Image (cartoon, coloured by chain):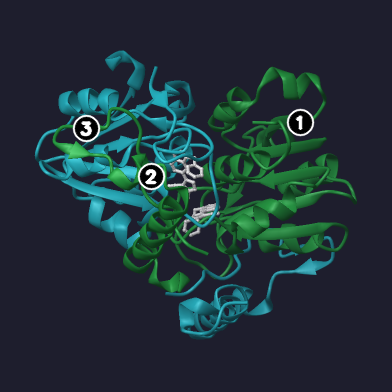
Chain colours: A green, B cyan
Amino acid sequence: SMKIDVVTIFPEYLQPVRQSLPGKAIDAGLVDVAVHDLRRWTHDVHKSVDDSPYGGGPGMVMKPTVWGDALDEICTSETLLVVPTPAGYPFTQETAWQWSTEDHLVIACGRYEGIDQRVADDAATRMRVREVSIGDYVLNGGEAAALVIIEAVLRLVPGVLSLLEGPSYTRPPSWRGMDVPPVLLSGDHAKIAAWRAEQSRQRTIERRPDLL
Amino acid sequence: SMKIDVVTIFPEYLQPVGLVDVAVHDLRRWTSVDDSPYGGGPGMVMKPTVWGDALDEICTSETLLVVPTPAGYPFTQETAWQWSTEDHLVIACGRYEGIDQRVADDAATRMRVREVSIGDYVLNGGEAAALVIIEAVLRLVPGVSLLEGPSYTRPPSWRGMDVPPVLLSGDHAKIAAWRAEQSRQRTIERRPDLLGFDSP
Ligand SMILES: N#Cc1c(-c2ccc3ccn(Cc4cccnc4)c3c2)n[nH]c1N
Ligand SMILES: N#Cc1c(-c2ccc3ccn(Cc4cccnc4)c3c2)n[nH]c1N
């Protein structure tokens, strides 16, 4: 049973997640994903969520007072607050496994230059906070990262949704001049396992030498 | 100017998407898309036949064929810069255990093909990776190291937490140095590999 709350100024971006969820898992009370428009917690008629950065620089910073009110309402002491950020700790499969047994994830999606740091720092005094990055590239905001995190985590929750994997093949045995490796059709399953292991070793050397 | 075509059995997942156009295609338009793996194993493999017909129609020899896969080369900001000046990206999104390897191999005989991974975690398919790649690339299209440090805005005091006084000082050199120190401190703590140190 996991609850995920996502807070964002672009609620529509999280539409795929809602679609990804099988009815059986929702009906069994195994998972609930709710998406919240950050502007519900704005203070002014202009529904302001950002303001100029102290110390100067380009871009804007999301307002602490708005985020503070949102997280005050949504989070409890048991919440794991997830904050995507290009400056975060790396989100890995190990992370996904750890988070898959949490009762309550709240994902705070920023835009612009990010969220005033006091939001996370204040929250960390009353709950667990994790600033994470999904990879070494730059996005426009946290929403695509939330999609990735939600999928990676929920597929590890029962019935909700190292070396590199080698190539896979299926029918037909010959296609556009290319035959499936004959070893795979040999019925020698110890040999097939060794062939697959060597394919994986070769691919890891070529594509991810860092893993070795 | 860039054209992006995305091919998927779940076109609805791509909904979050003048100098750039993005089109989404249902792979099933070219047909059962999957079958059991040769050599055994759990799960299913996407058939090369359907993919071949799809890519035949959508791709040219100019196309950069992008194939998300957990076994890919890393997609990084460098990749995003490289791809930002391409005329035509086609992103082939797999499901199940992935796509028959011959699809990429066949395609590489007539176009440039890039198998890439957006990170060291496992997804159920290529679609979320496609969304990440598109976002990272499009923001670099003409006409559109170290970890960044913390940012602050008004009010200068909030819940008894102050904005670092240097940021209020108006001293550009001191502000630049404090920010450099914050960034290097964050990088050592969170991504020591970026500075050539062992990971945790
Ligand atoms: N996780 C993760 C990320 C993000 C990401 C996450 C949240 C935000 C909120 C704003 N931006 C834009 C921005 C651009 C430049 C500097 N600072 C901020 C975000 C980028 N980018 N790349 C990742 N792997
Ligand atoms: N880029 C990227 C990815 C993917 C990814 C991309 C395409 C597909 C097509 C199917 N699956 C599920 C699957 C699961 C396990 C083994 N093999 C395949 C995909 C996962 N996962 N993690 C990433 N960083």
Task: Give the secondary structure at mark 2.
Answer: strand
Residue under the point 26% across and 25% down: B49
Residue at the location (67% across, 39% down)?
A154
In depth, the one of A178 and A77 nearer the eye is A178
> On what subunit does the disc labeled 2 rest?
B
Q: Is residue A15 left or right of residue A42?
A: left
Name which residue type carries label 2: Pro
Q: Is residue B194 left or right of residue A202?
A: right
Name the image quarter holding residue A202. bottom left
- Residue that numbered label 2 is attached to: B68
* Residue A161: image location, x then y, percent: 64, 31
Which chain is disc 1 placed on?
A: A
Look at mark 3 in the image and give the residue it sits on: A174
Alpha carbons under labels 3 and 2: distance apart: 24 Å
Q: Secondary structure at mark 3?
A: strand
Q: Is disc 1 on the same chain as disc 3?
A: yes
Q: Give coordinates of residue B93: x percent, y percent.
A: 38, 35
Viewer-side residue, B190 vs B163? B190
Vertically, is A90 above or below A172? below
Q: Is residue A182 visible?
A: yes
